[PDB]
Image: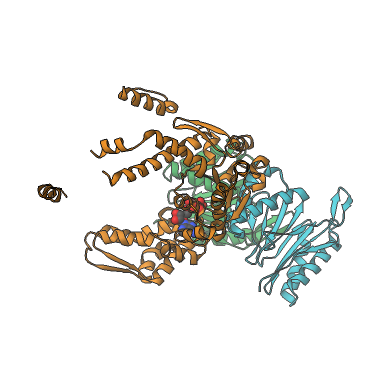
Chain colours: A green, B cyan, C orange
Amino acid sequence: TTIVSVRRNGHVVIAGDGQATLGNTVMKGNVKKVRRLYNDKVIAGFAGGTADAFTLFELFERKLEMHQGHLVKAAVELAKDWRTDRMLRKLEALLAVADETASLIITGNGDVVQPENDLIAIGSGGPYAQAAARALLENTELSAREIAEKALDIAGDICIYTNHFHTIEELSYK
Amino acid sequence: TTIVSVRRNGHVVIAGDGQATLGNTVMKGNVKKVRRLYNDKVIAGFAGGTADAFTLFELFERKLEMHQGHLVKAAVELAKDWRTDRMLRKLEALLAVADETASLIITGNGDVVQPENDLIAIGSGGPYAQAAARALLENTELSAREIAEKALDIAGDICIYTNHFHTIEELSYK
Amino acid sequence: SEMTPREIVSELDKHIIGQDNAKRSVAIALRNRWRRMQLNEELRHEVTPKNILMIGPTGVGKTEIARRLAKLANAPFIKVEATKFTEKEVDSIIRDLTDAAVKMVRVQAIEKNRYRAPSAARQAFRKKLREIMAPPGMEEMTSQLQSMFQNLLIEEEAAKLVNPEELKQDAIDAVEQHGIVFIDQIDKICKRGPDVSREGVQRDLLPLVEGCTVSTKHGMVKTDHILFIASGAFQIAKPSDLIPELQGRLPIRVELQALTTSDFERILTEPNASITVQYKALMATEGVNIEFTDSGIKRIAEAAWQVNESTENIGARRLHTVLERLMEEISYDASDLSGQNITIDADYVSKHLDALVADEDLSRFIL
Ligand SMILES: Nc1ncnc2c1ncn2[C@@H]1O[C@H](COP(=O)(O)OP(=O)(O)O)[C@@H](O)[C@H]1O
């Protein structure tokens, strides 16, 4: 699994593969690991069980309603409830989320993190994509969509658990 | 255990073996892992404890009655309560179900999945059956029944946990 | 009333559309009432009402059958939610039924006293003429104490003509003989395997159907021959989940079918005082004349069916929310449109609704 997020020129994207591995076999190659949230104002991705994220994403939208859509404050409240609830603590996933404000990562340990250039790369192939995205972001004028696309394909060629099936959700704010 | 589902030419089937393994021994070779539901309009299979599936099947018919037999929406409500309820969370099984609309998989993680060609293959020998069914479906004009039958026999020759006792429930809609 | 079962169903067809099996079932129970009175002294005590259990999704007319039935027989009627007692005493069912029977026989007594309520100069003028604070449980008690303390021409004549001792004794006989009770959503008190509290409500309701006596300020009422009509979707639980003492007290069972798009088309027009007829008279009050095309009525029924299939199926109740959303512009301008004839064609229906029905996220709020 690999998920990338790039922000550039008033645009932010989230891209992820569709491979689902069971042991040494591929279970499904067209998984949709990226989706939109909070009435199309927020994009998000997840590395882990599909229903684990659907549970966390729904509660995250409820945290946004209590906080008027504030991304950071709602992300902490989600991370606080994630570690705290005996039922939510059983969940195992790596969340990635972004809006026009900023991009950040959410983990099951309750750690909320915003990478240096809002450059998120998670999953088994995350570190692969992160180095490809870092190279293009500094040495090219490519748009955030072009970087996340090419970086995800590179991670698919390298990671055995990542394929070339792609799903993207761009957000333009300019 | 291996269970296959194929859909072709207005027909959809579900086939499963009858082997029940206890450690390194065979406990029962004529297990009926396939049955019909919702007044003969739905076919389903299960890989796991027999009683765990009977419980999930009955509740699945309840969700179908609330949703007027809609397969997808009832599958989400079943996967919703499966992960949620402290009682149902203890159940461990892999459900497969299909109607004339579509075929899909249900898991104890709450994940609902529809395979690419509605081609389901679950159990310990699932990957072996998916390899054979994928070959025949693209290279032959064989009916869905002949594909699921031959694919399950090949999975039984390979998987030590799968035998050649078979149970099938076809649904014709044309 | 001496109406035969077919005469009962024929009258119910004037309001309820289809669901004939439920109409036939209630007609049998009401006909046994008249059949019991013709029996000898012994059999009248042994025979007990054939209580009915309606089964089906919400909004298919389970209540309207019970309402029109009690309105057809001029019988006292009450609807109760079985879940209300999961947290009031069950005996309140008979009390409120009598209070409704009292007001029923009382306003009916005024009707008998209403019409009761010469020189040439006599006819000429005749032509020109034409504090006590209590907790909520005893609030009704302190009412009676306050009315007792206060005690210690249409009004004076109707009070002079009425017989208050007769109206109170009659309402009891109207309840003991002709009474009807509707217990909605009885399926929700069945065991889900709360089961103690759910089945505990079933035990508390048991004496009311097994024949018991309930005290009331209006008098002592007996629940022996009262008819009861329970209802429930029974999608979660089944009637077999009811306690055995309760299953035997509901001899008649019936399943109401889900309404179709054609039924919605009929419900909008055919029933007497149908909702479409209601707004036609309402817009007539403003001097406006509305007319619905058969294609317009068709797409309205098609619109309500889509919302029930898209999100949640609420039965024929969806027709109410849709129709008011369609006529909202006319109902507001109806004052300024006096003297105009407005037509609700298929294009008018698609103009005000298709934009809404297309968005399921909005349909969960507006419709
Ligand atoms: N067969 C029918 N004929 C006419 N109107 C109906 C019919 N079924 C439902 N309706 C309308 O829909 C509503 C049904 O609500 P109700 O009968 O109280 O729900 P339930 O049937 O679930 O108890 C009523 O307001 C009634 O006007």
The outermost residue toward the bottom is B141
| Residue C11 in the figure: left or right of residue C228 | left
Image location of residue C100, percent across then percent down? 42, 40
| Residue at horizontal 66 percent and vertical 50 percent from the top | B59
Left or right position of C335 against A71: left
Residue C185 x %, y %: 55, 46
**Residue nearest the observer in this picture, C184 or B95:** C184
Q: Nearer the viewer, residue C326 or A68?
A: C326
Which residue is more in the foreground, A143 or C108?
A: C108
Screen quadrant of the C terminus of chain C = bottom left
- Quadrant in which residue A132 is drawn: bottom right
- The image quadrant that residue B44 belongs to is bottom right
Question: Which residue is painted at 58% across and 54% down in the image?
Answer: B66
- From this view, report whether residue C299 is shown above or below residue C29: below
Do we see residue C309 in this rendering? yes
Q: Position of residue C106 (x, y in %)?
A: 37, 40
Asked if one can make out residue A122 in the rendered structure from this viewpoint, the answer is no
